[PDB]
Image (cartoon, rainbow over all chains, first blue to last red; front, side):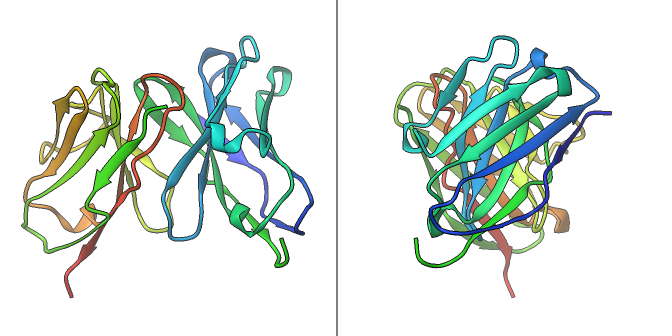
Length: 119
Length: 108
């Protein structure tokens, strides 16, 4: 069985950074793209970017350039998402997902990040 | 970059009704289009890929169609389990963007 387990919820301050993690089991993350997807409360899915853990290649939506950094650790079958310079607009559930150009069949349960006021 | 224009954003409907959700890409995406369903409180689930191919266990009342820039998901005679949100996504050039979503809600 494929599973993507995601890290626990984050309560963080404006201006800080946070690193979210997603650990895969039931497959090798080198064999597919791994993606991060943002969903603000009661709003839509937003593709942040992806990493190819086979070679480390990343692609991002330009709107997340600098805000988001995706990395992979193949030895632990884990991918990470660092979010920098946090503001209220970053309050969201962040999903990790696996797949390529035939759609993403596997999704983590998401990690809620709540940024407190002032940013 | 290619963006997806999804309509309608909100749709009220009743069990047994037929509804159509559309997604228009800002450039040709060559049938590399998926539809996802996301139930309240849950993660998205892949419903359709390659514009028209049903994913695992998806009932025949769902139908994806379209080509070029213009795609649609039709739900024939919708069922109690079909309420929730729907999203299209393309996989042509990166970024692999989502449509803004459709919230399919029961008429009360």
